[PDB]
Length: 74
Length: 440
Image (cartoon, rainbow over all chains, first blue to last red; front, side, top):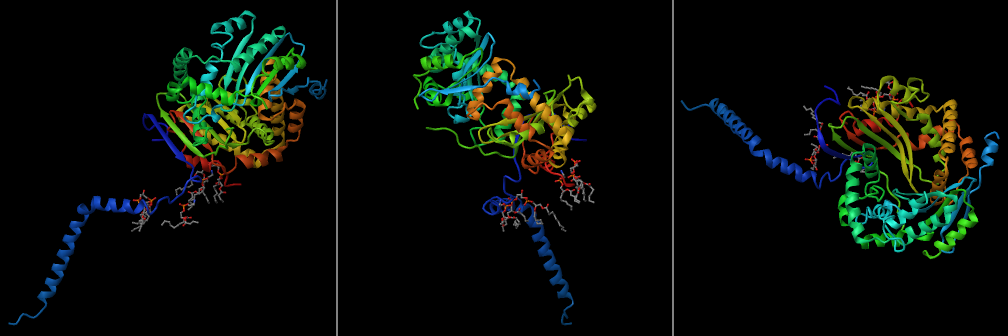
């Protein structure tokens, strides 16, 4: 697998700029911040709920375990 | 003569001017034939996006009839004397010329003035030429070199009128009207921007009298030229159905009047040219030519120094199969670097000899001399004699070549065009890194 014999491709034009003609951080905040927020809404309900469940399970297990070492009057 | 006395014995280009500002220039010989033409400071770089293609359209309609010579009549006249009418257009220049017998110069001159002054621009002919120009656009699509150089101009001069093609986009071809073309002629076909050149058995006094009798009507004594920013950039059109890939790489080179052109041309002669139909092959003094012949790395490569008034394309075009583009880049950029850092006197001597030979051999016949006169008066405002070109070549050495190739090539962003099976055309960063050496 080498460049020059990977696939057949046709009718695709690419335009690129020199790195010395352009900037390395264009619209890094004015565009980057909305993109991070978009990428966060896109995945948050797929990633977060399992970790919320872990937080609740951890919280419950720890408080319960410590609720067993307490003296029950008897 | 000893080539120093032969240069000193070359006939002198005589230049005059009409009151309207039309310049008249002629190099006389004892040949029984002459070439006489009009060269105009008009091109596609003078067109914007709405008019782009108008100059090529006007060149198309040039011989199709004037108010005095309707339709084929002009052609008949030319053909009835054995003369040959030709025309061409670039991004900066336009030319109309006749190859005639020396006794046909009056009529030839008359035929030219009419053509530049009184073109009919008839709407029926405009539609017929619309169809012709569309078919010629599709014909030009078949020529990979023409496409790759249009691509190189488009990416190197993006946003500028030098990125424009001569013919314009096909949409403009379909939309250009008679009013568009009449406006183009009225704003660009002016006497101060025209040069009436003649080379051959032509007396300058007689040509001047002809120009005063046929061109004196023209504009007496305004939008023209903005500089064109160069851009390091790449345009890659991949079509793996194409058998061979075309790659053109150029840095920003000097404009017309820059003396750096003479050493840079010398340097290009050091790299030279090649195609697979060469006798010399592996024995060629050019390193790239011998490597390409030994390894069969390419079908051809050429160096070029394209000049405009204020900038230009200094570089190389090569054609090769899909699996060798990378190699062709590596050995080409290396040659550039080898010239910037370690030029060496003997190959500078060879390149100087090549340049002198190119300059003398090019000017063989009345037509090349007529073009030299017209284009030279447009680009330099003067015919530079071959003795002067020799003086400028003689003052080139390996230090000069090293310095100028450093100034233009070393650590510079190139513009790159790739067309065809170009997957192995190296990524722009890799080429850009190939434009400098870490050892140096």
